Length: 14
Image 1 (cartoon, rainbow, N blue to C red):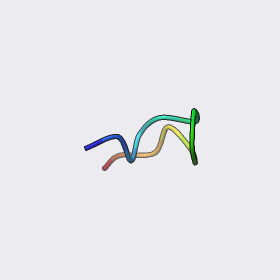
Image 2 (image 1 turned 120 degrees about the vertical axis):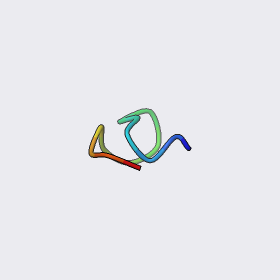
Image 3 (image 1 turned 30 degrees about the vertical axis):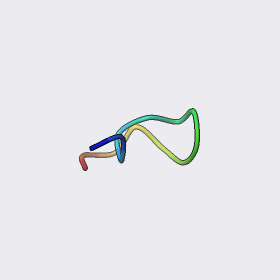
């Protein structure tokens, strides 16, 4: 998933 992309949120893990 893009959960780890600051593009929308933050470059966490998911």
